[PDB]
Amino acid sequence: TTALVCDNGSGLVKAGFAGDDAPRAVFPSIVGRPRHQGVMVGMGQKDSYVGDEAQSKRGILTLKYPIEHGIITNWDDMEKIWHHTFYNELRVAPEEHPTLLTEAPLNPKANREKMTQIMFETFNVPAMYVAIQAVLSLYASGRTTGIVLDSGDGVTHNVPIYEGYALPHAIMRLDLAGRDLTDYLMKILTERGYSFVTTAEREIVRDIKEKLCYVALDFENEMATAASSSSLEKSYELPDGQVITIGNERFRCPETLFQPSFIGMESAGIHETTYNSIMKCDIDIRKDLYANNVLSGGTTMYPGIADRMQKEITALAPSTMKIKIIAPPERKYSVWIGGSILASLSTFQQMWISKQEYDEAGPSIVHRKCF
Amino acid sequence: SDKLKEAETRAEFAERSVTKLEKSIDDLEDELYAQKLKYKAISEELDHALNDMTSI
Amino acid sequence: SDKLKEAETRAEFAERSVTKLEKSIDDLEDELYAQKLKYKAISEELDHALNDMTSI
Amino acid sequence: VPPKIPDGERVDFDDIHRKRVEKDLNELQTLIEAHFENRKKEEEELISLKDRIEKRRAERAEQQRIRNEREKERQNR
Ligand SMILES: Nc1ncnc2c1ncn2[C@@H]1O[C@H](COP(=O)(O)OP(=O)(O)O)[C@@H](O)[C@H]1O
Ligand SMILES: [Mg+2]
C-alpha cells in the first residue's frame, strides 16, 4: 500500500500520500473553543473547530496553537488535530497506512516517545517512522551534501550534512522563527496607532507580514530612505475596511532574523549561526558546504532574503570561497516533498518501526536502531 | 365596494412587484460586488507582478 | 372609506417607491456593465500580453 | 549507538529531471491553454450579455416612461 507522509510542523500541517509533488491538504494547526455564550438553539454548534474551519469562524473563537516551539505542549489538542487530518482532510483510515512524521532536531525525548505511543495506540497505524526535518529538505533539493537552514514557523535549525554523513556536533538550533516575527510586527504596528490584541487578530497581523514585509538588502540605507521619501508606504485593507499604511515597518519586522537583539534575544542572526555551524565542521568539507548552502522552510520566503544572506556570508567567509545559496521556488513544501521522496524509496522500506517491534520494546524503541 | 376591490388588487400587484424588484436588486448587487472584489484582486496581483518585475 | 383611503395612500407610496427602485436598478446595472467592460478591457490587455508570451 | 543505514544501490539527483522537466513544459502549456479557454469563455460572452441586458434595460425604461405618462395623464385631477 501507500504511505502517509504527514508533517506536523508548527503553524501549517502538511499531509499527503507518498509519491506526489505537493501535499494534498494544507491547513493551519489551530484548535479554537468558542468563548461567548450562544443563544440560538439547534444551530448545531460544536465544542471545538479545528483546522481550516476555525480560520473562518475566528471572530468568536479563541484559537490556540498546540505546538509552541517544535515541542508539543497540549497533547489532547494535537491528538484532535491528527484525527482531523486523517479522517476529514484525507479520508483514509490509519489502520492500513504507514506514517512518516517529522521532528525538529534537538527536541525533548518525551515528545517523540509520546508521539509514537499515540500513533501506535490511538490511531493504530501499521508502522511509523520519525525523521529530522532538515534531511528531508536536503532530499528535495536532489543534493547529497550541503548545510540546510530550515527556518520554519516554530524553530529555526541549521543541520550541516556531507556526503550523507550528518555532523551531530554542528547542529545550531535557534528558537527565533515566524511566530516571533509575527509578535514583533504586532508590537511595532502600535507605533502608528493600530492595536491588535485578540488571538484572532494575530492572524490578521500574520497576513500583513506575509503580503507586505520584505528583507532589506542594506538596513541603514533603507532606514534612511524610508525616513525621507514615501515610496515605500504600502497600504492594506483590513477584514472590515479602514485601510492601514505600513511605512518602515515593512523591512523592520523580518530584520529581526539577522539581529535577534530586536526582540531581546542574545544570539546572533541567521546570517552568523550558519557561518558558525560551518566553522565547527572539519577543515576539508568547508568549501562544499559554502557552495551548497540550502534554504528551506516557510519563513525563508521573504522577498530579497537570498541576496541579503549571501551578502552577509560573503562578508564573513574568506574571500576565495564561492558562496552560493540554493533557494528553490517550492521552498514552503520542500520538507514534505523530501518526505515523499524518502517514503517512496525501496531501500528505505525496511526501516519502518513495525508494530510487533513496538510491542516488544515499548515506546522507547524510537531512540534505538530504528531512529 | 367596486372601488375597494380594484384598489386592493392594484395594491397587491404593486406590492408583489416591489418584493420581486428587491430580490433582483439583491442578486445583481451580490454579483456586482463579487466582480468588484475580483477587480481589486486582479489589480493587486498585477501590482505584485510589477514589484516582482522590479525585483527581477 | 377608511379602507380605500388607506389602500390608495399606501399604493401611492408603493408606486413612488417602486419607481425609485427602478432608477436604482438601472443605475446599478449600468455601473455593473461599465465596470465589467473595464475589466474585459484589462483582460484583453492581459491577452495581448499573453500573445506576447506566446514567445513562449 | 547511532543508527546504521543498510547499504543500497542508487540513486539521487536523477529524479530532479523527471520531476522538473515534466512541469517545465507541460505546466506552462496547460496553463496557457487554461488562460486562453477562460478568456474566450468569459470576456466576450460577458460583454455581449451586458449589452443584451442594457438593451432590455432601455426597453424597460421606455415601458416605464409610457406607463408613468399615461397614468399621470389620466390621474391628473
Ligand atoms: N509567502 C510568505 N512570505 C512570508 N512569510 C511566510 C510566507 N508563507 C509563510 N510564511 C511564514 O511561515 C510560516 C509557515 O511556515 P511553515 O514552513 O509552514 O512552518 P512549519 O515548518 O511548521 O511547516 C507562517 O507562519 C508565516 O509566518
Ligand atoms: Mg518545517
Image (cartoon, coloured by chain):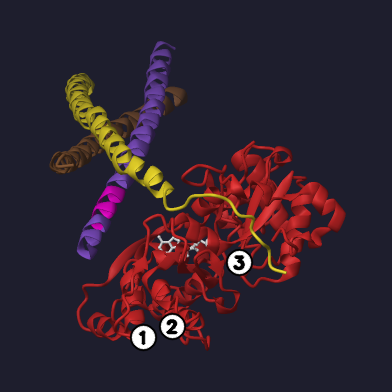
Chain colours: A red, B purple, C brown, D yellow
Disc 2 is attached to a residue of which chain?
Answer: A
Q: Position of residue A114 (x, y in %)?
A: 76, 61
Q: Is mark 3 within 8 Å of ligand 2?
A: yes
The structure residue drawn at horizontal position 34% and vertical position 38%, both measured from the top left corner, is: B29
Question: Tag 3: residue type?
Answer: Ala
Q: Amino acid at mark 1?
A: Leu
Subunit ID for the residue under disc 3: A
Q: Which residue is mark 1?
A: A316
Residue A102 position by quadrant? bottom right
Q: Type of residue at label 2? A: Glu
- Where residue A347 appears, as percent x and y from the top left, is 60, 48
Circle nearer the viewer, 3 or 1: 1
Image mark for residue A300: none
Do callouts 1 and 2 mark residues in contact (Cβ within 8 Å)?
yes
Tell me, for residue A104, which label it has, or none.
3
Q: Is residue A132 left or right of residue C51?
A: right
Residue depicted at 33% across the width and 44% down the height: D21
Q: How many marks?
A: 3
Q: Circle 2 sits on which residue?
A: A272
